[PDB]
Amino acid sequence: TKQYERKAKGGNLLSAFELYQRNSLVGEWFEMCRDYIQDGHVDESGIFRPDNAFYLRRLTLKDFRRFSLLEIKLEEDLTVIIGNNGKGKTSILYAIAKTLSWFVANILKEGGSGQRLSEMTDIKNDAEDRYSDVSSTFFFGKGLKSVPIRLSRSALGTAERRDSEVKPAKDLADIWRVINEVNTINLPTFALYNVERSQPFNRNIKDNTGRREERFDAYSQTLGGAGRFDHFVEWYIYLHKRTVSDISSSIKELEQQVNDLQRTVDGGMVSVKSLLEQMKFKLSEAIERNDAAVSSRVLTESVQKSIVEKAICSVVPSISNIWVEMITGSDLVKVTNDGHDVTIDQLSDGQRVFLSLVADLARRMVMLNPLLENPLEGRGIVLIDEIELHLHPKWQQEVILNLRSAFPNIQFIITTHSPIVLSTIEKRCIREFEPNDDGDQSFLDSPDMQTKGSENAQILEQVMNVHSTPPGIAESHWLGNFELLLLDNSGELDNHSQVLYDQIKAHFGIDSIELKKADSLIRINKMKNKLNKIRA
Amino acid sequence: SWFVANILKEGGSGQRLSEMTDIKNDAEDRYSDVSSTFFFGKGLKSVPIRLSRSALGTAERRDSEVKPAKDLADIWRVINEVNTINLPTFALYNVERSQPFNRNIKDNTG
RNA sequence: UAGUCGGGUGAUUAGCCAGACUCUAACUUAUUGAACGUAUU
DNA sequence: GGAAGCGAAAGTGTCGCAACCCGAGAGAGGAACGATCTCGGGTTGCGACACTTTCGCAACCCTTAATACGTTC
Ligand SMILES: [Mg+2]
């Protein structure tokens, strides 16, 4: 109508799409939708930025599990959830993953269904209303500032049923699906990495049926919690084989075989006609696949391989190189780890688990963003539980910075209990989870203290409520006691203070921080007393 | 199954006739109907239900008529929520009831 | 026996009384339209 | 007819298990090596069940109705 036309010309994506669907100026509306999704600019740092960003803004949980009512505001870039009560933290990530299942389902199939809330486990046990709600609001540029979705479930036997409200999510996912069908676009990545990602590696890898090469394999088990590192390895070996081979040589060889078979049928051998028809079909299929590959605007296998290799080596500190070796009629992925060439099964658990996360994520981003110069600059939402899992302090100090550098437009929602990780993150990104004895909280608060660039010891005390020295060790209190003894006299070493000083010296050593502090205390108190005498 | 579904949930869905097996093989019309009337006292002498299905392939599709079942089941459900009432039992025991027993298998589902 | 029909009574959609019927076998429905009854004209 | 959300019905694919095979290795009897038993890695077939697809219940009442009271369709 004229109203839709005005709104569409004003930049409203849904109105433009509705006009496109009714008329199917059809070309103009299609172009407007496609430009809304694809337009973007390269910033001063050389990073591509979409003009219309996609992220989760807000989440509300009503009578869900232990929560009566909980509201969370999320940052566009990075949100970190902290707290001792780690079972509630995981509940929050589960709620988000279920919501994201609705986008994935509808990008894959018209009328796709995402996941539903459980009547048994998701409804709070003492809920008066006997239903549960998970409400989410997404943002997609100024044209679509609010995309609300609600997942709901009522108890059995209630007077009224509580149904989910998913139409806005489906409408948006439909735009992505339909526009992509006509003309390839870049698509959003959704992924969940739970503690399940720590699992051992099956060294034996499965024969390539060729599901892994299909673009929408990027959405396979993406919200399951462990990634699919096995799928990566299969896909990566596949890429290697194609790079070493020529593409269309099989077509040229098949073309030659069909030509040879055609000559035989022309020479009077009618018995081989059935075989010719089969080979012609194979040739047509190969050309079609080639054409579809050509039509799908996908990156060359060589380029795909290179992108992923770079990503892995950049993010995973111990890995400098990754490649496929053809040995013993069996393809093996090898890595240079800490300067030495090893198989994946020879890596440490910390290295393997982190490698698996990054490899999985990069594979999916490459598959879903074929039109970007750097496919890892694509859009998406990634959930990571216990990011510090298996990581040494040195890696904890770099992990968030490395991830954000490799995937600059992903919205990361993470959980941690690491002060070292928190030292690299702004307090605005931090949400603290301090529930009551009933496990129930209303809002999640940012800490008072700035964490980014702060000392770890301060974060421990001010944010995580942990003393810098272990309270259950006597020696941890000696310097405090020593100070008290000095203050109880004028500030002179009495017999008691001297004994303790000697104990500190004996235990911690002559050049210990503890002893230096004691020495400092003596010196300052002596100087205070001298001042006092001069004044008297 | 339509009464049970609607006692459990407002607008619950009961079961359906099979389009593969339940239509009579040599029926000239390619659909089946199962029509039932229930009685619930002199204040509700007739609760008619019809389940219908057209054969697989057929272009015309025959609709079920289940609203009376839903209407009655709504009364049971709503009245019960305000003040507890006794509810009707519906059960089928077919020849599938003869099964091996297993104490070790437990249902962790509800 | 049960179900059904219904003459009466009953501050009356109940209850009670009387009489009767029985193909395997009623389940009381829908307007502003149409038709029928009543009113108005 | 059939919105939007939902689940029944029916077909397909995945995946973990159990059974089995094989070569390696320590080393019984007393000098001649290697008997017997177990480790550890791999292959195969099976079947339970997770995933996928399709159907179908029935909102709304289209710009467009009349209004004395009843009954029927
Ligand atoms: Mg009338």
Image: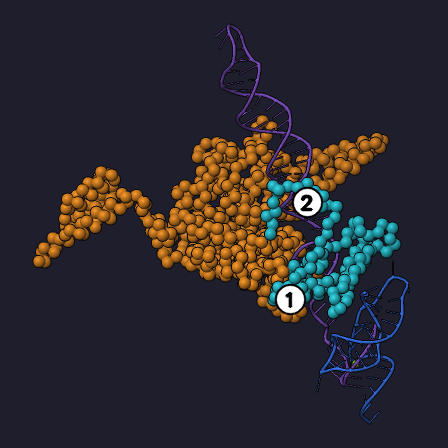
Chain colours: A orange, B cyan, C blue, D purple
| Residue beneath disc 1 | B79
- Does the beta carbon of the residue at mark 2 sit less than 8 Å from ligand 1? no
Is residue A300 among what the camera can see? yes
Considering the numbered disc 2 on the image, is that residue within a helix, a strand or a loop? Answer: helix
Tell which subunit mark 1 falls on. B
Considering the numbered disc 1 on the image, is that residue within a helix, a strand or a loop? Answer: helix
What residue type is disc 2 on? Asp
- Left or right for A284, reference A236: right
Q: CA distance from mark 2 to mark 1?
A: 64 Å
Name the mark on residue A376. none
> Would you place residue A313 above or below residue D22 in this image?
below
Q: Nearer the viewer, mark 2 or mark 1?
A: 1
Q: Residue at x 50, y 35 (%)?
A: A335
Label 1 Cα neighbours within 10 Å, binned few <14 / some 14-19 / many ≥20: few
In percent of width and height, residue A147 lies at 57, 61
- Left or right for A284, reference B77: right
- Image quarter for ligand 1 equals bottom right
Q: Residue at x 37, y 53 (%)?
A: A463
Q: Residue at x 24, y 46 (%)?
A: A479
Label 2 Cα neighbours within 10 Å, binned few <14 / some 14-19 / many ≥20: few
| Residue beneath disc 2 | A291
> Would you place residue A417 above or below residue A1 in this image?
above
In percent of width and height, residue A5 lies at 64, 68
What residue type is disc 1 on? Ile
- Left or right for B51, reference A464: right
Task: Choose top left, top right, bottom left or bottom right for residue A132.
Answer: bottom right
Q: Residue at x 57, y 39 (%)?
A: A230
Residues indicated by labels 2 and 1 sit on the same polypeptide chain: no
